[PDB]
Image: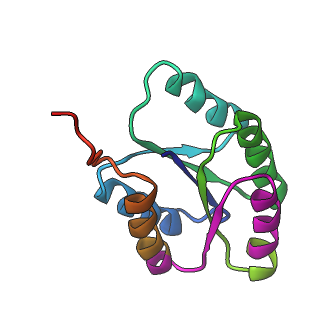
Amino acid sequence: MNIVIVVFSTDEETLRKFKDIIKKNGFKVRTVRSPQELKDSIEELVKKYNATIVVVVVDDKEWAEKAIRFVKSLGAQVLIIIYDQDQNRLEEFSREVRRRGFEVRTVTSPDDFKKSLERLIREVGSLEHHHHHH
């Protein structure tokens, strides 16, 4: 199943690690910087659904809300990995995302993201479909 990543780090270096670990597994990436950049992903998915992990890059927690408020409108079940340097923020924003029916996973360091992503990808469903009819 699909997965979303919310990054509070406006610094490219941190996001770079995330993008590298993703493509490592063979998945495509979309870094959202505007609301239409999120919706437009769905506009594509309804036409062609290929393995693309959408990473919403946020500068504040309400802009992060804006994204989750749209995803809430989608209704589907997706895993949401969020990164922030303050547990007070990260863990509390997690409250909202989780309450809205989305199982959110919080990461504090690139290596912790690396490990957790490797796990989730194999659990939720990787590019390796496994169950084949042939």
Asked if residue 18 is positioned above or below residue 62 in the image, the reply reads: below
Span highlighted in magenta in the image: 91-112
Residue at point 48%, 18% (across, down):
47
Seen in the image, is 19 located left or right of residue 84? left
Residue 60 seen? no
Q: Is residue 125 above or below residue 15?
A: above
Relative image position of residue 26 (x, y in whole percent): 29, 50
User: Which residue lies at the image location 67% right of the left edge and 72% below the top edge?
Assistant: 84
Residue 77 at what x, y percent from top left? 62, 46
Tell me if residue 24 can be seen: yes
**Is 115 in front, or is 134?**
134
Is residue 19 depicted above or below 37 in this figure? below
Check the image and report above or below for 90 versus 34: below
Q: Position of residue 131 (x, y in %)?
A: 27, 44
> Is residue 100 located in the magenta-colored stretch of the structure?
yes
* Identity of the residue drawn at 68% across and 31% down: 36
